[PDB]
Image (tube, rainbow, N blue to C red):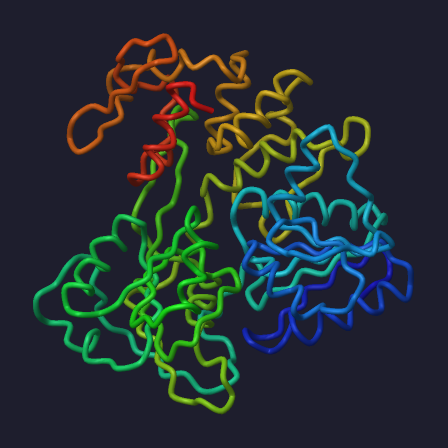
Length: 435
């Protein structure tokens, strides 16, 4: 696996021990061969788990999620997917790692897709080796892969709203359930319904993940309500997964705006990863998987792969060359390679709008490529009237940095800046110049 120009897809089934059994052996061999190695964790939660699996090994943990004092002589680096891509984009030296290991390599967030494209390009150039660790590589058609113990798969109507009757099987269960919902707002309504029924519920989403995931270990719970983020190696002591089999898809309309289309079916990979939360204990057969819809390849035209090209077009590889997307997922977007390449100053604005600004990739690109500097927020208010952002059926309002109360009406409308209360709150602060 570790020889140059080789990209290995480590596709053992979920729970087969890729992270805690195979990965330490890979690291030991890479250290023995003096291979400068990077390990890429999807989340800070997974990064902490890796330190436990790699404990004792000389690994430099480039994340505050791991409290360790370093030897200084480490040739293996561990960081999150997003960190790797962020450092590639910034004016910062990133080592040309001889071995690139990405765990949970099915992650479809833009920075993860970009990392896979950059890494696979360096391998294709004969410059490095790569190992992608995931049971569900891009394009897989198997929603029901092998597991450590048998799983009861049942197609069943799954609530996506509050219910009063007709779903007794949901609440009659006595174990612990992980419930994959299409959106934060959908999970809020289901969680409120379950709590009213006397169930203790924990909710997980991307923004709250690390803080809220700790609750699954520190307090007793009946249900975990989570978006698709729990497809990325989050592990629970559950005996049932309820899967709506649905997700939101960001879609760019006319190159003009981003909507959150759906809910619509998940991919086979996501369905397999959602189901893969259970059936993990070889001595505990009988875990249940209830799924409420079919699968489709809804990653085609999905904005994340367009956004991945926006990132890759602004990562230096060699002179004017631009890294291509990882081959199995390169057809998920109709993009002209290099069409999003920005000049030096606009690239820096693009980066800061994503890092400090916390804006979606697509939205940050629109602002930066328009020649707007990072602190210039006038574009948040001079859009067309149909771009008005609403907050409880009244137009959202903020005080501008000039002290004037104005309606939130961004020139470019990205539905992800207001998909829930927390996102809209963060964008209101941005439009007010508070970060």
